[PDB]
Length: 25
Image (cartoon, rainbow, N blue to C red):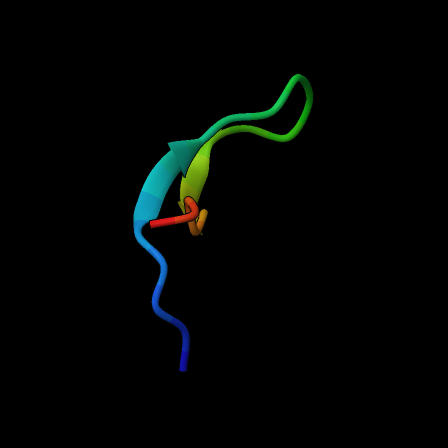
């Protein structure tokens, strides 16, 4: 599994969703 946090990732084409981004924390 991972140890990231979910963000409302958005695109220019396609749309937005829940992405585990993983910020260096």
